[PDB]
């Protein structure tokens, strides 16, 4: 079997920040309805790109406004139905420091993002479809990459400061890669999923920097396991065959130029690592794009933990989506273009999905 | 008086500095110990000229130089050499590690730990200098210290000093010959950071000089010394109008006002025509006409480009020795008659001329002859774009696959920093095309 | 002060290293007691790269020797140049590995890696600025491979910003010396490819060919091969210990020769070798050294570059020579033989020159090549591996010491993926 499924690519333009208002960088980015085009401030070679979905939250009032729950019901809700059809799901973000990846995926206390909405919709839509025909089983995993190391977000540490216990990745011959030691804890409803997200977004590495004071210094990956029985009636015992889902929602860190959000030591070490990671991922995307157009290429999954564990998601067997974040200021021009250009590569990538 | 602070940034720079300082010492009369025996006979004179040397009451002449390499192997050859008693001992090595052919190491990880000290010694020097005209930096696109450290320093000096001249002498990479598989990148990025700070970046290349030394001087196996001695001579022509007397003198503030039309097209090329051996030193008249024509021959350039594929925007011609000016005017007119030397429509003058009465000094052990007159030509042309374009092509062939990039990101550089750079250089290339288009009414 | 800390593990490692110290003592003028008995001053300017001063102008090296059995350790002591090593840096236990990787990585070697790391931390904090490490070991056994790889892991954890170079005798295609070469080699590749920054691959058939059809020696003992490996070891690190017109430390070489992080496996070579009778029939100049260095008969990797393409080549010259010669001849190599060089790297060459050559020659050169042909090695191992792993040929000696088949499958996958990387740059488009 097989299904040539493309990766659905969304883009969002975040509004101004406070420092961006101080230095007064005026509008450079524009949405022609859904098409996105950018303007160097010296009227230089106006650039234009097109994407499967766009979002313009630059101001609450403009026509074409597009907010958190719209992003949700446009991309994440489809993927929930696919997670119900019998597949695994990968939506992954990209951007730079202060660009809104954390706001778009997870969100704030009052205005939460794709993660709680996916979970809540899953629970409500399950309890609407939970009868003695098909049961439902759930557990949650949430991990982070920091300085090339893996760490479990839902495991509180014991009484000593550096107790941040690292794990290791391993390659199962059929199932592909995985993480050893991941305290995948068990859930039934929305409340304990919420307590887990609490403990995770608290344990995630953050730091104050020269762009946002609650910056993200770690990649974060969100994967719930959701099993629903396939109710056979056979000569013997029933209900043994089963249809599974594993989620993937990925919130990455920023590119971190070392002169603007500048620091020395640890705050500079981790930055390097982040960028290294990002670089490798770019190659993968680029490479996969060439793979869709006949070129004979090799995907360097193994030069990073992130792209190594997402091997069956960037290609492989999952329903796929990218989300890019951009800011409206000249400061970001090439970075934005880098962002935008990577999406246009991710538009062209196709993987093979299968019912579980 | 008129004073200059030479800065030698890297291996190429230090070795060129050694050549230059040997020659300046020979010209003025300074022994390597710092002593000038010339006042043994003539009292009340000035030959240990204050532009390049500083005098203590004890009769010494210490240079105004700053040497910087981020590796001890090259300055220690001075400290333990024949010129150990000349340079101030503060020759800056924090060279516990070099830059590993990396602008990222030379601009951020090991770009710092030394630069504050550098600026301190520069400040100490300039405070001793009353009438300072500018700096002259010697570096090399191809390394780290010569690519990134130079950039950082230029950035800082464009703040701390400002309205001073900051000229450069660089070894531009060659199209074929090269000693590094990371040169293109470093070149592009250095050009990005320096175009907004430097004022005139004289460029040389070693392939051209190899070929010169082959044809004219009859050396088929030359080393690096035999090259830098030529480069030394070039500076000695630029710097003569501060040190020696003359008819028409050119200070450092007079190049960049004539050889630089727009602020981004300040990449001129050098040449020095009578690179003639002692055998062939005879059989030649060595007149102004011969030399001025030679300085326009493409085969006598020091940057591998053909001016016949482009247009001259300006040319400064610096003459040394027995030269009468009528001969210059006749020579330049001959050149302006020729149709192979195609000047722009918006520079109907084109030329600048400077003359000095002190002829060149033959370094003993050398490969060039004693001439009565010598000439150095600094020319701003459009051909060098081709050269720039070549680097850009190389860049693409590598950056399309992100080769060698994880060494840069590893030393605190964002991927985008590359792209920006390339785009800027593209602009520059477009700007060169804008200056070749004939004007319309 | 760019300093190196030198480790050497196992029989091969210790014998090579001993022959190495007897080659970098001869260059630096140190005697078997530690004292300086030299000619020049430049021998002492930069001796700190490898040695430390002790008391009476005696120089004690920064050697860390490791064995899981004491038989090889007693030979270095009871030998020429053993009375200069620091006795507290002979870290050796009993319970040999058994030509088994497990006993060196998990059982007996884990009972001794802490000792080695203590000696390291002593010989790494007594250094003003460390450039990195270098290990001489042997893929093919247990102690060298196992304990070495483990130490690599632990140093790249403790000292991450630094170099970890390696000189490794890789297995040979025709004849072996252990029946469990494949497994151990695959696991060592799995643990090196992720950790090291340069891996210089040596193969003994290449060195026997060198000793046969070039040097024309009828009795090639191992002391001769190690004398060829030492020659490269010295050539790689010259420019940190002698001056030159154009210098090249290790990190520069790596930056130029490592485009992607995992393809850091190099075919080495040294020139000039003249057999003792073809001395008076051969001129000593750059064209000859270049003709020899780029010949497949002078390379140590046992892999014909003519079956691939050179991603990146490096030439460290020693002697008074013209740079024009080097640049010209290199460009000539690239142009005449363009089918053996990558197109998306315009200049595939790196040059270094030093001024102080070897004791008996006017000119010397070392060559480091990154070519795709290295696949021909690993590919073979994988074939061997799977031809055994399909039947559980010898695995019960491994599982019995705390291992699982998962690691074997992992290592196979990694090595094959590496082969594939080196393949995608083999054809001409
Ligand atoms: C009459 C004469 O010319 O003797 C030469 C000689 O002819 C040849 C054979 C020497 C000779 O090398 C060998 O015979 C040999 C034997 C087994 C394995 C490898 C080589 C020589 O033994 C080797 C020796 O090499 C050196 O002198 C270097 O200093 C060499 N020294 C050592 O390796 C060394 C070993 C143990 C103890 C002390 C020094 C060296 C090479 C590389 C790096 C550092 C040092 C030299 C010049 C010669 C003889 C003696 C014949 C050559 O050796 C090297 C590596 O340069 C082989 O080709 C070179 C030059 C000559 O062909
Ligand atoms: N003309 C000339 N060029 C030189 C000389 N020495 C080195 N070069 C050139 O310098 C380039 C490499 O730059 P380097 O000076 O070696 O780099 P660096 O400034 O030392 O910086 P590092 O690599 O970190 O040591 C090469 O392309 C050479 O052509 C020299 O003596 N004369
Ligand atoms: N679309 C939006 N509309 C309004 N406010 C936003 C929007 N996106 C982000 N913000 C605010 O921007 C602030 C910083 O954004 P943030 O989500 O931290 O960026 P980020 O994705 O975390 N990048 P990094 O921290 O480097 O990973 C948050 O406090 C949000 O409240
Ligand atoms: N070049 C060289 N190779 C050696 C020497 N001794 C052993 N070997 C090689 O080492 C391999 C076995 O490694 P070994 O030294 O036995 O590892 P150990 O038993 O774990 O210490 C074989 O393939 C040999 O070819 C030596 O002195 N020189
Ligand atoms: Mg964030
Ligand atoms: Mg250097």
Image (cartoon, rainbow, N blue to C red):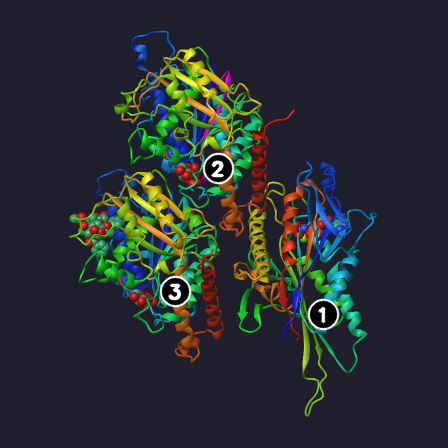
**Was residue A250 drawn as part of the magenta stretch in this picture?**
no
Closest to the observer: C224 or B220? B220
Instruction: Indicate the secondary structure of the residue bearing disc 3.
Output: helix
Q: Is residue B312 visible?
A: yes
| Percent position of residue C217, x then y | 18, 59
Name the residue tied to disc 3: C376
Name the residue located 39 percent from the left edge and 67 percent from the top edge.
C185
- Camera-nearest residue between B432 and A303: B432
Q: Position of residue A291 (x, y in %)?
A: 57, 61
Q: CA separation, marks 2 and 3?
A: 40 Å
Ligand 6: image quarter? top left
Image position of A24 with respect to B240: above or below: below
In this picture, residue C103 sits left or right of residue C291? right
Q: Nearer the viewer, mark 2 or mark 3?
A: 2
> Which residue carries the number 2 mark?
B387
Residue at 29 percent across and 61 percent down: it is C206
- Dot 1: chain letter: A
Boundaries of the magenta span:
B127-150
Judged from the image, the secondary structure of the residue bearing numbered disc 1 is helix
Tell me the residue that label 1 is attached to: A82
The one nearer the camera, B265 or C103, is: B265
Q: Quadrant of residue B412?
A: top right
Figure quadrant of residue C323: top left
Q: Are marks 2 and 3 in contact (CB under 8 Å)?
A: no
Q: Are marks 2 and 1 in contact (CB under 8 Å)?
A: no
Q: How far, Cα to Cα, is label 2 from label 1?
A: 55 Å
Q: Position of residue B294 (x, y in %)?
A: 39, 24
Residue at the extreme top = B43
Up-down relation of residue A109 to residue C69 (above or below): above
Towards the viewer: B377 or C255: B377
Which residue is painted at 64% across and 59% down in the image? A348
């Amino acid at each position: 079997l097989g299904s040539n499924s493309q990766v659905t690519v969304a883009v969002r333009v975040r509004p101004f920040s406070k420092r961006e208002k101080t230095e007064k960088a005026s509008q450079v980015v524009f949405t022609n309805g859904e098409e996105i085009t950018v303007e160097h401030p010296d009227m230089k070679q106006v650039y234009s790109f097109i994407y499967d979905v766009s979002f313009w939250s630059f101001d609450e009032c403009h026509p074409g406004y597009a907010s958190q729950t719209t992003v949700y019901e446009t991309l994440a809700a489809p993927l929930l139905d696919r997670a119900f059809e019998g597949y695994n799901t990968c939506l992954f973000a990209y951007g730079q420091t202060g660009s809104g990846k954390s706001y778009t995926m997870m969100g704030l206390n009052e205005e939460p993002g794709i993660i709680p909405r996916f979970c809540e919709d899953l629970f409500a839509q399950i309890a609407k479809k939970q009868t003695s025909e098909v049961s439902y089983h759930l557990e949650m995993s949430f991990f982070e990459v920091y300085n090339e190391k893996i760490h479990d977000l839902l495991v509180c540490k014991g009484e000593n400061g550096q107790r941040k216990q690292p794990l290791r990745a391993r390659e199962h011959p059929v199932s592909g890669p995985y993480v050893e030691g991941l305290s995948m804890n068990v859930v039934s409803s929305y409340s304990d999923i919420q307590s887990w997200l609490e403990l995770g977004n608290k344990q995630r590495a953050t730091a104050a920097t020269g762009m946002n004071d609650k910056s993200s210094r770690s990649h974060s990956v969100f994967t719930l396991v959701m099993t629903q029985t396939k109710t056979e009636v056979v000569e013997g015992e029933e209900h043994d065959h089963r249809i599974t889902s594993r989620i993937n929602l990925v919130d990455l860190a920023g590119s971190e130029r070392c002169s603007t959000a500048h620091s020395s030591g640890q705050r500079l070490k981790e930055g390097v690592s982040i960028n290294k990671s990002l670089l490798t991922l770019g190659k993968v995307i680029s490479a996969l794009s060439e793979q869709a157009n006949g070129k004979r290429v090799f995907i360097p999954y193994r030069e990073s933990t992130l792209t190594w564990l997402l091997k069956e998601s960037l290609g492989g067997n999952s329903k796929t989506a990218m989300i890019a974040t951009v800011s409206p200021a000249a400061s970001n021009i090439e970075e934005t273009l880098s962002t935008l250009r990577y999406a246009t590569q991710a538009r062209l990538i196709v993987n093979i999905a299968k019912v579980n | 008086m008129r004073e200059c602070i030479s800065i030698h940034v890297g291996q190429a720079g230090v070795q060129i500095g050694n050549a230059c300082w040997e020659l300046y010492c020979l010209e003025h009369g300074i022994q390597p110990d710092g002593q000038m025996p010339s006042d043994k006979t003539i009292g009340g004179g000035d030959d240990s000229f204050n532009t390049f040397f500083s005098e203590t009451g004890a009769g010494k002449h210490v240079p105004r130089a700053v040497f910087v390499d981020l590796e001890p192997t090259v300055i220690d050859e001075v400290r333990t050499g024949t010129y150990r008693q000349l340079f101030h001992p503060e020759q800056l090595i924090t060279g516990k590690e070099d830059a590993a052919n990396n602008y990222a190491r030379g601009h951020y990880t090991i770009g710092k730990e030394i630069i504050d000290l550098v600026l301190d010694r520069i400040r100490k020097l300039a405070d001793q200098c009353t009438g300072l005209q500018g700096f002259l930096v010697f570096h090399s696109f191809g390394g780290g210290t010569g690519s990134g450290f130079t950039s950082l320093l230029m950035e800082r000096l464009s703040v701390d000093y400002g309205k001073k001249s900051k000229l450069e002498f660089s070894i531009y990479p060659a199209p074929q010959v090269s000693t590094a598989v990371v040169e293109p990148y470093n070149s592009i990025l250095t050009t990005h950071t320096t175009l907004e700070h430097s004022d005139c970046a004289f460029m040389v290349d070693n392939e051209a000089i190899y070929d010169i030394c082959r044809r004219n001087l009859d050396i088929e196996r030359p080393t690096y010394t035999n090259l830098n001695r030529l480069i030394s001579q070039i500076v000695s022509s630029i710097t003569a109008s501060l040190r020696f007397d003359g008819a028409l003198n050119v200070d450092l503030t007079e190049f960049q006002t004539n050889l630089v039309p727009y602020p981004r097209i300040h990449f001129p090329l050098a040449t020095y025509a009578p690179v003639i051996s002692a055998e062939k030193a005879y059989h030649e008249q060595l007149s102004v006409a011969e030399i001025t024509n030679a300085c326009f021959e493409p085969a006598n350039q020091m940057v591998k480009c053909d001016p016949r594929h482009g247009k001259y925007m300006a040319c400064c011609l610096l003459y040394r020795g027995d030269v009468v000016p009528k001969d210059v005017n006749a020579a330049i007119a001959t050149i302006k008659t020729k149709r192979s030397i195609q000047f722009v429509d918006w520079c109907p003058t084109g030329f600048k001329v400077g003359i000095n009465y002190q002829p060149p000094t033959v370094v003993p052990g050398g490969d060039l002859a004693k001439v009565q007159r010598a000439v150095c030509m600094l020319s701003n042309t459009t051909a060098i774009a081709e050269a720039w374009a070549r680097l850009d092509h190389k860049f693409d062939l590598m950056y399309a696959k992100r080769a060698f990039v994880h060494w840069y990101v590893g030393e605190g550089m964002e991927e985008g920093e590359f792209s920006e750079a390339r785009e800027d250089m593209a602009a520059l290339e477009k700007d060169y095309e804008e200056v070749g288009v004939d004007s319309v009414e | 002060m760019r300093e190196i800390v030198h480790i050497q593990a196992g029989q091969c490692g210790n014998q090579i290293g001993a022959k190495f110290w007897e080659v970098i003592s001869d260059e630096h003028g140190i005697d078997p007691t530690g004292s300086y008995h030299g000619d020049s001053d430049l021998q002492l300017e930069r001796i700190n790269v490898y040695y430390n001063e002790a008391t009476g102008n005696k120089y004690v090296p920064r050697a860390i020797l490791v064995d899981l059995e004491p038989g090889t350790m007693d030979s270095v002591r009871s030998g020429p140049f053993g009375q200069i090593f620091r006795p507290d840096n002979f870290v050796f236990g009993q319970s040999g590995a058994g030509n088994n990787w497990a006993k060196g990585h998990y059982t007996e070697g884990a009972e001794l890696v802490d000792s080695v790391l203590d000696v390291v931390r002593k010989e790494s904090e007594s250094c003003d600025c460390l450039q990195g490490f270098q290990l001489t070991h042997s893929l093919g056994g247990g102690t060298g491979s196992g304990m070495g790889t483990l130490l690599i892991s632990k140093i790249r954890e403790e000292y991450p910003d630094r170099i970890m170079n390696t000189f490794s005798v890789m297995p040979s295609p025709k004849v072996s010396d252990t029946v469990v070469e494949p497994y151990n080699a695959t696991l060592s590749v799995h643990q090196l490819v992720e950790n090291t920054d340069e891996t210089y691959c040596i193969d003994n058939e290449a060195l026997y060919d060198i000793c046969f059809r070039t040097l024309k020696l009828t009795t090639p003992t191992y002391g001769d091969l190690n004398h060829l490996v030492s020659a490269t070891m010295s050539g790689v690190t010259t420019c940190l210990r002698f001056p030159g017109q154009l210098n090249a430390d290790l990190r520069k070489l790596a930056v130029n020769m490592v485009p992607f992080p995992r393809l850091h496996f190099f075919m080495p070579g040294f020139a000039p070798l003249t057999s003792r009778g073809s001395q008076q029939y051969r001129a000593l100049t750059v064209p000859e050294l270049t003709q020899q260095m780029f010949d497949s008969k002078n390379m140590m990797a046992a892999c014909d570059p003519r079956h691939g393409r050179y991603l990146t080549v490096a030439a460290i010259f020693r002697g008074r020579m013209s740079m024009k010669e080097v640049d010209e001849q290199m460009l000539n190599v690239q142009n005449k033989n363009s089918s053996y060089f990558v197109e998306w790297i315009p200049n595939n060459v790196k040059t270094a020159v030093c001024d102080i050559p070897p004791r008996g020659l006017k000119m010397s050169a070392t060559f480091i090549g990154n070519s795709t042909a290295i696949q021909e090695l690993f590919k073979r191992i994988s074939e061997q591996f799977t031809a055994m792993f399909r039947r559980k040929a010898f695995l019960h000696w491994y599982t019995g010491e705390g291992m699982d088949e998962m690691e074997f499958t992992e290592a196979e996958s990694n090595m094959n993926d590496l082969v594939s990387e080196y393949q995608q740059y083999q054809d001409a488009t």
